[PDB]
Amino acid sequence: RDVFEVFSRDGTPIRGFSRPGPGETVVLVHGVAMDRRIWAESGFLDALPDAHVLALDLRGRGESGRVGTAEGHALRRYVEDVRAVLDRFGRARYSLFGTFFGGRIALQVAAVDTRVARAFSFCAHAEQVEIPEDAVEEEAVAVEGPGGHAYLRDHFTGRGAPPWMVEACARVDPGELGAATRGLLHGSDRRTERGHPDQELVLITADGDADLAPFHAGERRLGAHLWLVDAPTRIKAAGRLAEVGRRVAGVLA
Ligand code: NA
């Protein structure tokens, strides 16, 4: 692997790695309480034999620049972070894959950037949601204080998340956990759109998901394909991420 740096629109440095390969160029976008290490730890990276893989740390996570503000974590800023990565590698076609909120980011990049030929969203849908302000603030306070890492570790352990997803939380600065949570009030509630007719859009979730309806809504509205994995909840579906990677490799082949 090689390391790279690019700059987002607002000046924030975005750091990542490039894993060279002769196949399709794939850009991987992690979730909120995660960083770029989850791709190897989950087995997703190993499931792509040929792809040229670009994996970024989103702002405020991993080796990327600090933010520390709610508006700095708006969805539109994360989209700008990903588009900067597309610029550096100079291709006309990319395939994006995102986990949880990273899937929502990938779908929004697809809506606005004509270089995105494929976008896959793992355990996140594309529909408008209602985001209650009081619930957001309650979660931000929970995750940003001295007890915030223990709060998240206990939450994810009790919900059966894979060990890599439990452990990633303690690698995120408490202040960025709080700010990213508040950033949800700056545009993430709106639905995402199809960027162009030839794009391939894929949603993935647990067959047991308690709220499959918004996934079916994206099939209809966006012409997206829906993939299911054997799991009773979205958090437990993360145990199937390498399996999903094998099916992604089949599309890229
Ligand atoms: Na990533």
Image (spheres, rainbow, N blue to C red):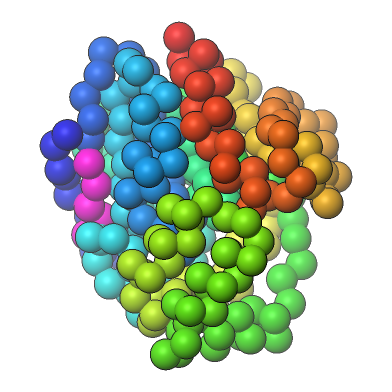
62 or 151: nearer the viewer: 151
- Per the rendered image, the range of residues in magenta is 13-17
Image spot of residue 152 (x, y percent): 53, 73
Q: Quadrant of the C terminus?
A: top left
Apparent side of residue 198 relative to residue 58 in the rendered image (left or right): right
Magenta highlight on residue 64: no
Which residue is at 30% across, 36% downward? 54
- Residue at (33, 67) in percent of width and height: 171
Above or below, 3 relative to 176 = above
Residue 213 locus on image (x, y percent): 85, 45
Question: Is residue 224 rendered to the left or right of residue 2?
Answer: right
Task: Tell me the quadrant of the picture where the N terminus can be found.
Answer: top left
Q: Is residue 65 visible?
A: yes
Above or below, 249 against 175 in this view is above
- In the image, 128 versus 45, the foreground residue is 45
Expressed as whole percent of the image width and height from the top left, the position of residue 14 reads 25, 55
- Taking the spot 42% from the left edge, 35% from the top edge, the residue there is 43
